[PDB]
Image (cartoon, coloured by chain):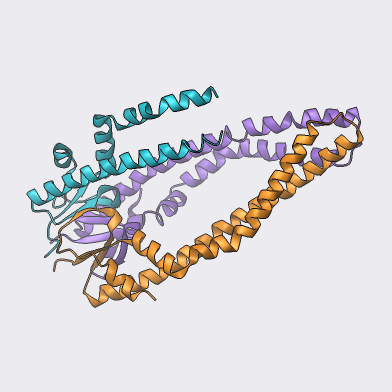
Chain colours: A cyan, B purple, C orange
Amino acid sequence: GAADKIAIVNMGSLFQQVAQKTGVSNTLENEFKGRASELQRMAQKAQAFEQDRARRSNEERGKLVTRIQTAVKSVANSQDIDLVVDANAVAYNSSDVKDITADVLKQVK
Amino acid sequence: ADKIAIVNMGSLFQQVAQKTGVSNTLENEFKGRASELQRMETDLQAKMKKLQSMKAGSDRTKLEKDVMAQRQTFAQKAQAFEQDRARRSNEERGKLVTRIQTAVKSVANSQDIDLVVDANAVAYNSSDVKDITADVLKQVK
Amino acid sequence: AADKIAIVNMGSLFQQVAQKTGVSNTLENEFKGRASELQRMETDLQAKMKKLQSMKAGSDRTKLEKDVMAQRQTFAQKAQAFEQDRARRSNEERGKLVTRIQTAVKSVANSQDIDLVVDANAVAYNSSDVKDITADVLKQVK
């Protein structure tokens, strides 16, 4: 079968851990505070910057997600896994359905 | 090969909320501040009705000061409330999502299911993939 | 005995079947009128709340206070009813698209002996021999 061996991965948990360890949200604070700082002082320009933090946080969102997907794929191919279901979509899994979360995290680049 | 089922975890969260009394626990617990608030709101209603029929005077100018004092009493009260019910709502939610999970596991070991996927994540399931929702509600404790 | 699994990208089908159907221009259209009235109602309302802060107290001030209190309650009841009209109409057209797409998902599945179609959303990885049926499903949507 094309889907013989299945696995689950905890995307939300990898997102969180990889964010913490890269600092992205610190970085995104630093990116912006000066422009908040010099505004809580000071306004259609609080909407030109509200739509900058969106576009950027999202952008940082995506880069982390694509780095984690790469990782899922390397671990799934390296262990001959055919499908990696997202954990948040799974209410139960047997041992025949391994959780690869920690293996995946270890490969994130 | 892996045997697979689905569970509707939205159509089940409300069924187990009723079944377990939690839905009504939360009800009983909040009805006091919810009566405090209704009372407070029609008191207002009727004061503002009064203000639509009062002449330029200082009686009216005053009922205006008191009704703009009541309007902030009913707003520190209405989101001390909305926040405390969303936050007990979360706890009651989190606590019984695990009742449900526990029931899902028992049902999956009963029926030899290796993977139970959430319904909202599936677009189609054949008759080889069982919807175990009703079986799960039966097992919830 | 192994169940045959495929994946379908619902968010893509939805946003493609939504375009082709014009539901979104149809909802903007259905509501831009009332949106505009409510906007104009708001800024004319602002103009009054401005001139009230401006006046010396007496006959005209209370007349203005009573005009505003009454417009505020008409506005609030109208914004409310526009929200529940938007929410519900969006809700319905959402459903209509869902149903039409699911019927397509069902026929392609039956036609290819598929047992479980997972939404791509929920899949972090799949081998290339587990089929993405988004395109076949799109072609069959009526």
Q: Give coordinates of residue C57: x percent, y percent.
A: 87, 30
Q: Give coordinates of residue C52: x percent, y percent.
A: 80, 34
Identify which residue, B140 or C84, lies in the foreground: C84
Query: In the picture provided, is C14 more to the left or to the right than C82?
Result: left
Residue in the picture at 78% in, 42% down: C68
Q: Quadrant location of residue B15? A: bottom left
Identify which residue, B40 or C89, lies in the foreground: C89
Q: Quadrant of the N terminus of chain B?
A: bottom left
Residue in the picture at 51% in, 41% down: B26
Residue in the picture at 27% in, 39% down: A15
The reply to whether residue A17 is visible in this rendering is yes
Query: In the picture provided, is C111 more to the left or to the right than B98?
Result: left
The reply to whether residue C98 is visible in this rendering is no
Q: Give coordinates of residue B140: x percent, y percent.
A: 35, 51
In this rendering, the answer to whether B63 lies above or below C109 is above
In this rendering, the answer to whether C116 lies above or below A82 is below
Residue in the picture at 57% in, 38% down: B30
- Total label count? 0
Query: In the picture provided, is C51 more to the left or to the right than C77?
Result: right
In this rendering, the answer to whether A21 lies above or below B5 is above
Identify which residue, C32 or B13, lies in the foreground: C32
Q: Give coordinates of residue B36: x percent, y percent.
A: 67, 35
Q: Quadrant location of residue C139? A: bottom left
Query: In the picture provided, is B61 more to the left or to the right than A35?
Result: right
In this rendering, the answer to whether A3 lies above or below A84 is below
